Length: 351
Ligand SMILES: CCCN1CCN(C(=O)c2cc(Cn3c(=O)[nH]c(=O)c4ccccc43)ccc2F)CC1=O
Image 1 (tube, rainbow, N blue to C red):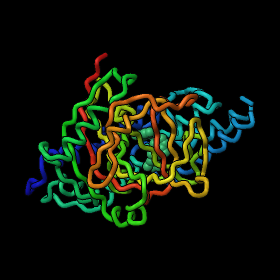
Image 2 (tube, protein in one colour):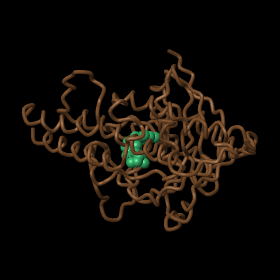
Image 3 (cartoon, protein in one colour):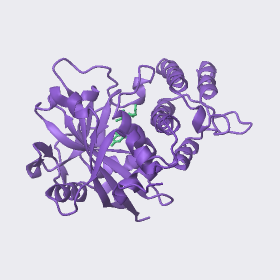
Image 4 (cartoon, rainbow, N blue to C red):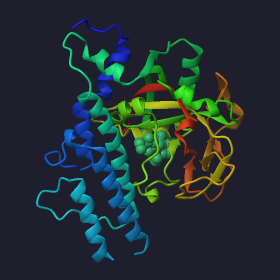
């Protein structure tokens, strides 16, 4: 084939995110039986139906029996086959079970998008599959120059906001990409001048990124159990890089991760200390801020293309009896996010 003119960093990004074996590896990490639910038999209606049963399990837990729970639990495993041999699988009888399974289904949604791009489309041997898969993302991806100002600011954001409690690893930035999802700037127009626009982190596993770049960061569907998400069903960001980087789920056996920086239109924040599984914001609010005990030093906020970058070292916020060690930001309308960068990260595990 004609060999692809894309920058090498862009080619390795495309290799990573469309890797079929990585998708499978993620699935067996969630204890899915690939013999019964292979990557190709995954579909949206199966994932949604599973979400609903998980909403049934949520209902039965909120009103307290291991007798009547058993039936709902089994119905879940019926829709998403798990790898337990001749079994009796573990009972899904608590809030932790619901959170953990909702998170798995979130990932399956993104994996199904990635695989549907791969199996949709055309076959032409004379094109480099790298170029072919790139086009499927409908996302302009450029390499940001190491010596630019934007690169310096980004590396400082990474350098300054790694929490002491996440010190089992550190981060080097391998590549910085500037990204522009088709139509996202247009979608963002209503919020582009809103106050309190902040450049924030969103980490995810590499097997979700094809989904993210083609479909954007998204709201979990109606069927998903609201109780599975600490501040309900929205799009979550952090101001501490390590808090987001934990969601990459890197390890000693695959240490390269991907993390986003999005411009988030937060406006009037509904400030919370503890879990609130809301399905709408109070009138007049545009976002939830989950209040951390620690925050980037607000005096070291810097501006990048008119957007605040909270890149100060972590200090005490002053908030007292909070569930959150660090800040968290949630929006509930997809149009409040404009994705700006994508970093490839090297994780040095010190353990
Ligand atoms: C439903 C499609 C896939 N999906 C999964 C849900 N989602 C989220 O942003 C989300 C993400 C998380 C977990 N999470 C996360 O995965 N990455 C983060 O950087 C993060 C930062 C602060 C708090 C949570 C974070 C929890 C609940 C969520 F709703 C956006 C999203 O598009």
